[PDB]
Amino acid sequence: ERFLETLAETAASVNQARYAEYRAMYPGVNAIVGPIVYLGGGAGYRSKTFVTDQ
RNA sequence: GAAACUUAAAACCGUGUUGCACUGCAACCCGGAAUUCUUGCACGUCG
Image (tube, rainbow, N blue to C red; front, side, top):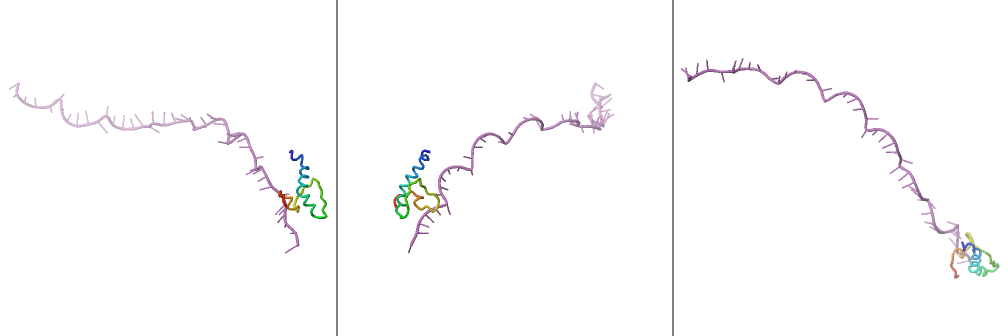
């Protein structure tokens, strides 16, 4: 329950650490900070794991 | 006084249901408690 009250916070902290720096490598893509999550197929290998190093 | 079987013959027998009437019967819950439950992205990879 205490985790669910800070759910938009951990969704933003996992956004800046997992795929904000990977998204900024490819040109023409503008980085958003967001409470961003990923859902469903076609989302990539990075969204369905917890591996850190490239 | 010594000498001559109150003897012989004759089933205590014949006939006759230990028989007649009578419910091993009346009353009684195989009943009371219990989640087919616990974990699991129809998804990953592109000369």
